[PDB]
Image 1 (tube, one colour):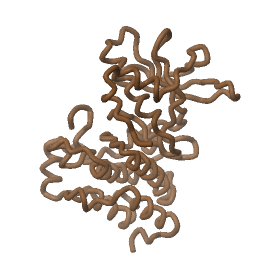
Image 2 (cartoon, one colour):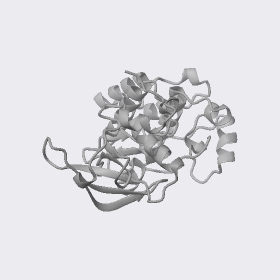
Image 3 (cartoon, one colour):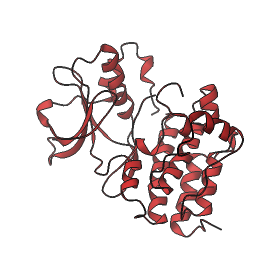
Image 4 (cartoon, rainbow, N blue to C red):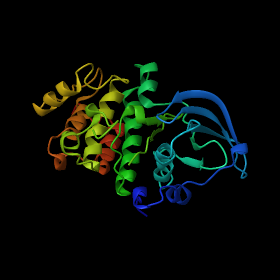
Length: 283
């Protein structure tokens, strides 16, 4: 059981039907817009589910009159997401591909993106709560990594949070395009060498984003200033109250030699020790 790059499929859609269960549109309720995506509005709503008990769902719509080269790309997310089954990876309920408005139906994550969520609750979570959010994200990325999937766009804006503060990896897509530089490893930006090692550099920024409560990595520095800065050995500092051991794990994630960075397996260990005791996150 390892990820099947859909793009080896010829007919792109055959991937959707293998990985993403088609749902009935009459079993889907839209209640609320909660965002907008590349392809159209993200809504909150309900699915059932014969089984029983309406399940709360996020619903990503493909806006009407899409091009063929948006129904392929938009539904590429389902083909990837539906291959995954882990508590710290957003769950697919299924898709709508024909005969009805095109949708991806995803488990409802009450608290939305982790970066917008932490800005609204600035200073409300202890280190041990924050360590826990990252332990989750790291558990997710270890599973995605063991499955041979490379995310390429790990950022707090692409992590979703439920009402128990369980953090889940979302936004499946596998600096080419939207992959912005301030989350990307130097060898991914310069050489397009995308790996789990480069996801770990990005995980390191997510650590900074979390401990800073949704501060923008590198603040207002231009992409070019961030690249020269990182090239000179500049690394971001410990946000307010962020223990030195957590910031140290950040710095190891941000080693310029990709093989010197910890694997997600080790990151989960270092985070568990820290939950279990100061760590000590300074000692």
